[PDB]
Image: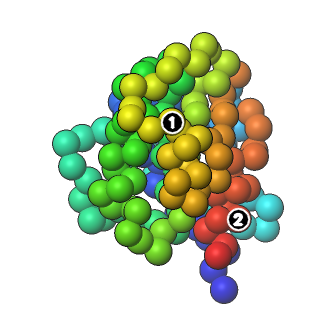
Amino acid sequence: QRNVFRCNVIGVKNCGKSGVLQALLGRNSYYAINTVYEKYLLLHDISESEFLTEAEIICDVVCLVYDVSNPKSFEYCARIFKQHFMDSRIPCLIVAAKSDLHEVKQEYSISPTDFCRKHKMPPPQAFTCNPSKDIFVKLTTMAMY
Ligand SMILES: Nc1nc2c(ncn2[C@@H]2O[C@H](COP(=O)(O)OP(=O)(O)O)[C@@H](O)[C@H]2O)c(=O)[nH]1
């Protein structure tokens, strides 16, 4: 019965990934850990690159992070999902980051809400560093399945 869970935080460069790790540590290093309700959630900051290694794919739960101010950020999340996680035993969560900024329409063929519903993912979770613990509990909860 594991109580320590690993989560890969994946998204476009400067989409607010490091903010998510710092938020878990309680703020407004590419790994961050803290207790979640007692469970331990270990986040991994996966920098944007050309491809992902099989060491960056394995985890207990995936946190796909896209930027609501960057219309090109969700396409990356959707592409990575279908390539590495759509055909996997790994639960996935999509987070609409920088929520406090204005939501410009994402340039993808499918809406985020539709895309999530299409692949049995929870609806897109809004998040900002300006911090709630909601996503980390859900990430941990989804890891406990
Ligand atoms: N408005 C807003 N800006 C943010 C938030 N989180 C991060 N940023 C800004 O986004 C920029 C890049 O974020 P960063 O953490 O470096 O993302 P990363 O490069 O993917 O790790 C930073 O200069 C932050 O000021 C947020 O929740 N709200």
Mark 1 Cα-neighbour bin, 10 Å: few <14, some 14–19, many ≥20: some
Q: Residue at x 58, y 34 (%)?
A: 96
Q: Tell me if residue 86 comes above or below residue 131 in the rendering.
A: below
Q: Name the residue that disc number 1 marks.
A: 111
| Left or right, 59 with reference to 56 | right
Residue at point 55% right, 43% down? 114
The residue carrying mark 2 is: 141
Image coords of residue 4 (percent x, y) = 62, 70
Q: Relative to residue 8, is residue 27 drawn left or right?
A: right
Given the image, on which type of amino acid does mark 2 rest? Answer: Thr
Name the quarter where the N terminus is drawn.
Answer: bottom right
Asked whether mark 1 lies closer than 8 Å to ligand 1, one says no
Residue at 65%, 65% (x, y): give it: 142
Residue at the extreme bottom of the image, as rendered: 1
Residue shown at 27% from the left, 65% from the top: 54
List x then y, in percent, for residue 99.
Answer: 64, 24
Q: Toward the viewer: 26 or 59?
A: 59
